[PDB]
Every structure is written in C-alpha cells, then in structure tokens.
Image (spheres, rainbow, N blue to C red):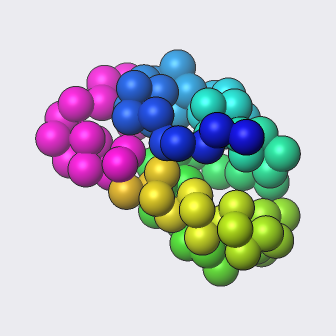
C-alpha cells in the first residue's frame, strides 16, 4: 500500500531489531517470516536475489527492499542509528 521507506522507522532499532515490524512500515511484513530470520544489519545488506531466496519472490517487493536497505545503511553509516540495534 504505502512502502515509501520511512527513514524514521528504517533507522529506529525498534523496527531494525524487529525486522517483521521493520517491514510493517514497508508494507512487506508479507515477507516478515522470510526476512525475520535475517537482522537489519544483514537485511540492509541483502539484495533482490537474496530476498527471493528468503521468500520475497515479487520482483517489485524485493528489488524495492533494496531501496530500504540503503536508507538504513547510510543513516547507519552516519551513526544516526543507535549502536544498540547493531
């Protein structure tokens, strides 16, 4: 529905530690079970291909998650994300 990649949630250890929840703000909780087994630090590092391997078969959904992966990384790179999430 939305999946506009909220830089607020994508960089809040609350969601990050709770990937499913992290996906909630991305409308990809659909793949929560497939992406839950993987933390944010790894999620944000995944790729369209890996996502497929998990369960994200939607070229639209996975390739899209790659957008959420970056916003998290950069902010993670800018120490904008609590080291607690790490």
Instruction: Based on the picture, tell me whether residue 44 belongs to the magenta stretch.
Output: no
Figure check: 54 above or below 10: below
Q: Residue at x 15, y 41 (%)?
A: 78
Q: Residue at x 58, y 62 (%)?
A: 64
Question: What residue occupies the far left of the structure in this picture?
Answer: 78
Question: What residue occupies the far top of the structure in this picture?
Answer: 14
The image quarter containing residue 85 is top left
Figure check: 53 above or below 32: below
Image coordinates for residue 37, horizontal then vertical, percent:
73, 48
Give the residues in magenta.
71-86
Image coordinates for residue 5, horizontal then vertical, percent:
49, 42
Instruction: Based on the picture, tell me whether residue 85 belongs to the magenta stretch.
Output: yes
Q: Nearer the viewer, residue 60 or 30?
A: 60
The image quarter containing residue 58 is bottom right
Is residue 37 in view?
no
Image coordinates for residue 39, horizontal then vertical, percent:
58, 45
Q: Quadrant of the C terminus?
A: top left
The image quarter containing residue 34 is bottom right
Figure check: 53 above or below 29: below
How many numbered discs, if any?
Answer: 0
């Amino acid at each position: 529905s939305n999946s506009s990649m909220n830089p607020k949630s994508l960089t809040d250890p609350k969601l990050l530690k709770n990937i499913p929840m992290w996906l909630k703000s991305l409308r990809l909780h659909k793949y929560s079970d497939a992406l839950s087994g993987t933390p944010w630090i790894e999620l944000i590092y995944l790729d369209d291909e890996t996502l497929e391997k998990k369960g994200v078969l939607a070229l639209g959904a996975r390739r899209k998650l790659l957008k959420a992966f970056g916003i998290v990384i950069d902010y993670k790179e800018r120490d904008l994300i609590d080291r607690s999430a790490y």
